Structure formats: C-alpha cells, structure tokens
Amino acid sequence: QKWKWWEEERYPEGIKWKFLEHKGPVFAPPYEPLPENVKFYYDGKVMKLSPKAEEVATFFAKMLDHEYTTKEIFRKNFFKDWRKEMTNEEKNIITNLSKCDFTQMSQYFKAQTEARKQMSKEEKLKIKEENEKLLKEYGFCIMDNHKERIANFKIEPPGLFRGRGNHPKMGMLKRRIMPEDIIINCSKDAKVPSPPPGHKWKEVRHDNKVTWLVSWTENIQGSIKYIMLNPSSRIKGEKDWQKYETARRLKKCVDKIRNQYREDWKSKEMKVRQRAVALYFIDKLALRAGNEKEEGETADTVGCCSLRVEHINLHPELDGQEYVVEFDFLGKDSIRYYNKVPVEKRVFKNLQLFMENKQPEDDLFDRLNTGILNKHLQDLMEGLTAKVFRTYNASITLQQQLKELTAPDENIPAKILSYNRANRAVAILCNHQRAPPKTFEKSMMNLQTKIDAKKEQLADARRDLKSAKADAKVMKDAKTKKVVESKKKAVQRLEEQLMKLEVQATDREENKQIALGTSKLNYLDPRITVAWCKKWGVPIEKIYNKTQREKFAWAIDMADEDYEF
DNA sequence: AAAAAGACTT
DNA sequence: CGAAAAATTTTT
DNA sequence: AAAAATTTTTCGAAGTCTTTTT
Ligand SMILES: COc1cc2c[nH+]c3c(c2cc1OC)Cc1cc2c(cc1-3)OCO2
C-alpha cells in the first residue's frame, strides 16, 4: 500500500479509533491423543489416561529434558494442577507424581520432532502453504480506513508455566483458552466476528478508547492478556514516536532537574531526600523504577523504588575509588545487577541515613514508591515518568557515541562495528545481559580459523607481489610495470576482506554477554539511527532487518541526515 | 488515599 | 525480546 | 550429500504507568 500515517493529523487524546473489524482470534490446535503403543506407566503397571489428564501428562513429558522438572515448587504445583484435571478412578490410583513413568511419552516426542526435520518438499511445503491461508484471513484487521497487521493472533496453547527466575507458580497448568474467556472489541458498525460453532464469546464490546482487539484473563497470575496490532501499525507507532519525542523533551531540561535533585539531597524533610536519591540512580545508572508486587505471586525481584536494604551495600574506599556503593540484586526477568558505583559525597552520606537502624528485609526507601516519584516527575516536566530516564539515557548515549566512534575514513563494515560498539554501550548501561549460547561458543574458533586462513591467502598475495617488484627492476615495460598494479590491487581486494572478517570477530566477542536486542527495538530513537545511515551512506538494511524496518518505517522516511535527538 | 484492574511497553 | 526450534545456508 | 555453524521463527512473561473499584 505505502501508508504514511505520520503525516496525518493526530487523534484527539484518549479516543483511539472510529472503526475496527477483525475475523477474531485463532485458537490453539485441539489436543491429539497418544497412539496405543505409547503407553503410560504408574507404579510400573500399564495405565491409560482420560484425554483431560493425558494432555496434562504430555506437557510434563515434553519438559523432562530440563533440570527444572525436579524442583519442589515445580513438582508441587504441577501435580496439584494435574489431580484437578483427573477423573475419579485416576484421583484414586495416582497418589504422588514421583511414581508415574513419562519416559515412554517423552521418547515418542523426541522422535516426532526428529522425524519432522526429515519430511521432504512433498509434505513440508504443504504446511507452509496452509499457514499462509491463515496469516491472511486472521492476521490483518481493518482499523479506520486501513488494513493493518495483527501481532500474534494465535492464542497461547495450554502448557505449564515456568516463567523467569524463581517463580512461585512454576509448574501450574495454563488452562486452554475457550471462546467463553474471550472478550472481542470492535466497532458498532463492524461485522462482529463469528465464534467457533457451539460457543459464545465472553463479551462483544465496543470500547473505542482502547487499542486491543481481543482480551482474556489468563490464570497463572490473573493478569489480562491481549491481541494487539503489529508494531508497524499507526496505533503502535504514533505511540512509540510520542515516547521518543517525550524522551527528547526531557533533554531540554535534564540539566535543570539534575540541578534540583543535586540540591534536594539536603532538604529539611527526609521523604524528599529519598525521592531525590532514587532519581539519581534512575538517571546515572538507568534503573527501572521498581513497582512493588504481591509476595508469593511473583519471582522476588526489585527495581529502584523497591530496593530492599539487603540489596545495597556500602564501602567508603575500595579498589582506589572514593565513596562507593556495592550494588547487588535481581532486577527485571531475574537478571542480576552487580555494580561497584562511585557517587557524590552527599549521596553516600544520604544512603547511610536511609539504612540506619533497619532490618535487612526492609525497604531502603521508606515512604517512597513509584507513585510518589512519578507524581514529582510529572510536576517537573509535562508528561514525564521514570522509564523516560532509561529511554533518554539510552538514546542520547547512542547518538553521542556514534559521533565519538564513526570515523569518515573507515569502510562500510567498520562503521557497522563502530555502531554495534555504540549499541553495546547502551546495553551495558541498561543492564541488557545475555548468557553466551549453550556450548555454541566454540564457533569463535570456527570463525577465527577462517581468519587464520584468509591471512594465508593474503600472505601469499604479498609474497606474489614481492616477486613482481624484483621483475619490475630488471625489465621495465608495458607488460611488467602494469602487472604489479594488478597484484597490489589483489593485495587490496584481500585486505578489505580480511578486515571485514576480523571486524566481525571482535563484534562477536565484545558482544558475548550483552544483548543488543531490547535496546534496538525498545530503547533508542530510530531516527538517531536513520540520520547516521543517511549521513555515512551505510544502506539502512545493514542495520535494521525487515520487521525492524517495518516498525521503524516512520523514521526511515522522515529523518534527514542532520537529525539530532 | 491504596488496593486492584487494565492497558500498554520491555 | 533472546534462547530455543525450525528452516536454511556454509563448511567438510 | 551429510555433518556443522547458520540465520530466521516460534515461544513463553515481567515490567511501567494509568484507570478503576473496594
Ligand atoms: C523486550 O521486548 C519484548 C520482550 C518480551 C518478553 N517476553 C514476551 C514478549 C515480549 C515482547 C517484547 O517487545 C515487543 C511477548 C510475550 C508473549 C508471551 C510470553 C512472553 C512474552 O509468555 C506467553 O506469551
């Protein structure tokens, strides 16, 4: 089509659409039972299970490979939830989990998977084709004059929850989502989608102030899950753009706030002193303002405002630095945040005051929570909140570091390295860690062997040139002195090759325990990127793949080479 | 308020 | 997402 | 061709902030 929505006038705040029509959500493929020969054993005696329970048994049989299926919490929860999905001959016989034998089911599944990567184009293409009849019928919805794409219209299948980290609910069954759980949201003038035969949707609402197409209540933590639009849409873009534009507004008066909190580290009231120290951490250390959460329903992890006392430790002078805080805690997605950080004299003397006669299990910031912090932030700048501090620090660091890295002289894949090194700088700030792929890091030897090979191809292009400079001394004609210029051009064509290969070796190494994923799509103004690519002639696709190009299709078209965040 | 939902964001 | 799978692509 | 290191998809939750209810 080619729809420039960024040129259109905005929508009067709070009203999100006028028209919304979609063929609804796609359900999970119905459960296909086990064939006779894949028997299940309880107490060593052959037991055949009812479809409800057998379904729940496969979920466990498939995860057997994992170390977590031995964890107490996991076996406790799972089993409690399996008993429930069992009949009475079964709730009588199957007393504990530990006496059931899934090994046969488990092996059948490892077989089906290996005997899937073995079908030829005769059966393989027939699936990739049937899937395309689907993405077309259910994957696009019409929202106000335009056919826009839906994110993940395919509803999540029932399995067992595991979640990240030490989740208290790990093991609990994720119930299959029936149409009687689904609320559809469309316009009054839209052709309301038809439910699967023999079912009704939970509600057909026309709430035009929301951007969601379908919503149901999932049951592990009782949170409301949704089916929203593709990031390439208007309803997701206007928004993302607003967010970077709000990140830019914070820049105009960032120094002003960094002056007031610097002075607020004095204040007569203790409660203002907290709200200021917290603000420093979020600013200079890019911390998620930690909202509090229900104990026993989430993995114990925290952010800034929820920082318990046991999570921070003081040190006056360590490893040569003056006035340091030894940060150690589990942040979002249970990823660790270890950092020895040198603060200002006041702040250190201010943290001591916050820990003074307090128990390890208690809050560092008493009578402070994210609500209070955001209330202040909102007074400071219209529309401000605490994530903007991570978006700004992320963006302003990508742009300023591209200026400090990208050299005019350098070739095209070297710019990519200078860029990736800037991207990296954000990821270390934002604590966007990654764990090096499971024993797949011997592929550093099989990328370095390609280099200690290209060094030999070029070793000899020089040794071949050194013969031509001993032949251009005795006999200096049109077919000698010009045969050197084609043997030096050959050293050059292989230099620019070895260089690309070696630049792509340190871009892989420095990035072994760092994830640039999140910062690329979620933090970082894409215009900062487009500006740079238009400026140094690096073709856009060398930085952004297709879904990233699609999401960022508003920036690509808009920003000039001169754009400055 | 201030818990508890809901709706976005990462 | 980003680690894990499926679909590819290079290496052997 | 067949193993081997890839590049692309699929999968499986946890945050922030805002708006409601009790
Ligand atoms: C960092 O950025 C993103 C991080 C994510 C992390 N986890 C999940 C999603 C994400 C989407 C992001 O950006 C768009 C979508 C999602 C769906 C799920 C789920 C986990 C996640 O468990 C069941 O269904």
Image (cartoon, coloured by chain):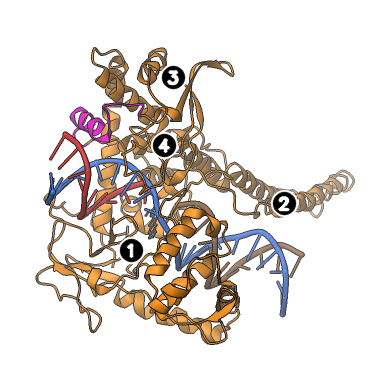
Chain colours: A orange, B red, C brown, D blue
Task: Determine the image quadrant of residue A171.
Answer: bottom left
Residue linked to disc 4: A399
Residue A381 forms part of the magenta stretch: yes
Residue A229 forms part of the magenta stretch: no
| Secondary element at image label 2 | helix
Q: N-terminal of the two: label 3 or label 4?
A: 3
- Is residue A37 shown left or right of residue A517? right
> Mark 4, mark 1: which one is toward the viewer?
1
> Picture coordinates of residue A309 (x, y %)?
41, 27
Query: CB at mark 2 closer than 8 A to ligand 1?
Result: no
Image quadrant containing the N terminus of chain A = bottom left
Q: Chain of mark 2?
A: A
Query: CB at mark 4 closer than 8 A to ligand 1?
Result: no
Q: Residues within 10 Å of mark 2 (few under 14, many from 20)?
A: few
Q: Residues within 10 Å of mark 1 (few under 14, many from 20)?
A: some
Ligand 1 is found in which quarter of the picture? bottom left
Q: Do the residues at pointers 2 and 4 share their chain?
A: yes
Q: Do the residues at pointers 4 and 1 share their chain?
A: yes
Q: Do the residues at pointers 3 and 4 share their chain?
A: yes
Residue linked to disc 1: A151
Q: Which residues are magenta?
A: A363-383
> Mark 1, mark 3: which one is toward the viewer?
3
| Secondary element at image label 3 | loop
